[PDB]
Length: 257
Ligand SMILES: OC[C@H]1O[C@@H](O)[C@H](O)[C@@H](O)[C@@H]1O
Ligand SMILES: OC[C@H]1O[C@@H](O)[C@H](O)[C@@H](O)[C@@H]1O
Ligand SMILES: OC[C@H]1O[C@H](O)[C@H](O)[C@@H](O)[C@@H]1O
Ligand SMILES: NS(=O)(=O)c1ccc(F)cc1
Ligand SMILES: NS(=O)(=O)c1ccc(F)cc1
Ligand SMILES: [Zn+2]
Image (cartoon, rainbow, N blue to C red; front, side, top):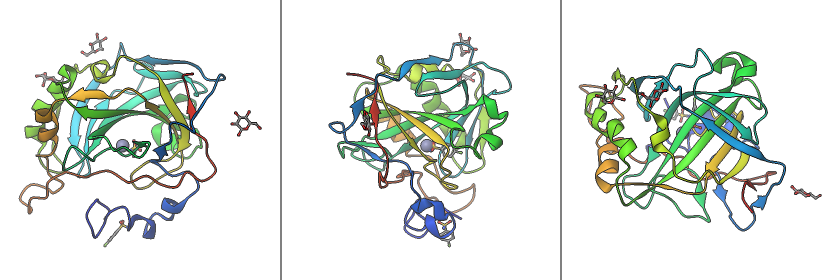
């Protein structure tokens, strides 16, 4: 199956997922000079006060922190979005070195990592139906740079030793995703896709302009995870990012003047 190595990485995905060469693939480079302020964007509302985290899972590609999405609890609304989008999971992409790891780039700059908070449009009833729709998903993307530690990330870091290999999971209740946000909600937005197979073109991307800072020690612990399963040859889970894809017939809009 697909992965990030030389033999199954992003340059091979199109052979099983032909939409990889589609018209609104993600990630993209965000040219900050060409991005235009959009006065039609409504205020963005990140409403995570009642979030119910459940579990953390190494899926062989990243680790997911999963949420109860059986009711309207942690939701994302406003901005470019029509209606209510429910948080289902978050995960990260990161590099082998601090100079790479993000999926989106900003004027071609690569950050050390990128956080994706994944939400589905409640009008479609379930995530599976949402990924059949052009406006089925909204992903809130947040860049990570290396500097001071992010206190709200530390609980994640300290559980990773218990999910080292593909297929392992652990309880992860009572985690507040609000501790992963920067101060500002200024953002760029554009229509795109999932950045992993099946690469479905269902996503409204909302990428925050302000990175969060994490410590070197925090990201070094991400890089101790394994792509492989228990008992298999160790393959460090690093460089699990897709490079920027062609913008094609899209514009990136900014929430800020
Ligand atoms: O425990 C993590 C979070 O869970 C939510 O359900 C609560 O409303 C928050 O106050 C809390 O920070
Ligand atoms: O025709 C003019 C319009 O062109 C579009 O490509 C831009 O997104 C709009 O902001 C602009 O008003
Ligand atoms: O909040 C996420 C997790 O953080 C820490 O690991 C706590 O020990 C655990 O009880 C909790 O589930
Ligand atoms: N197309 S892909 O899923 O990346 C893939 C690449 C190489 C394989 F051997 C099998 C699958
Ligand atoms: N990496 S991402 O675009 O946020 C993504 C989110 C949900 C998926 F099911 C697959 C990929
Ligand atoms: Zn992602």
